Length: 65
Ligand SMILES: [Zn+2]
Ligand SMILES: [Zn+2]
Image 1 (cartoon, rainbow, N blue to C red):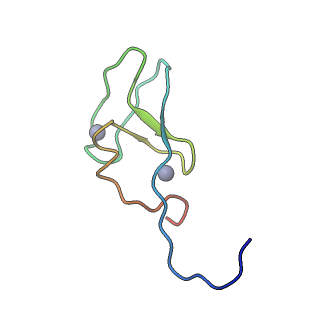
Image 2: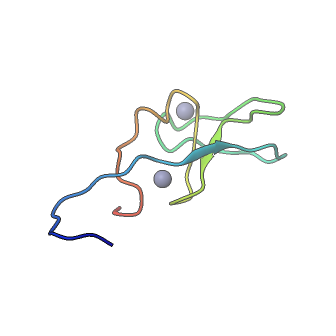
């Protein structure tokens, strides 16, 4: 909590590396990901799969959208 008032807020995508065996699709470049242990990244907040770079290209609104 806090003392005051807030308005508009934006949060980044909690993208965390994941080691799995499945065909993942990027929500930005719309392509496949070829990896071994760092198979792209997956947001543990909203739940999205994007590349390491394609991640910094997505909006900084996790949960709001
Ligand atoms: Zn997110
Ligand atoms: Zn991508």
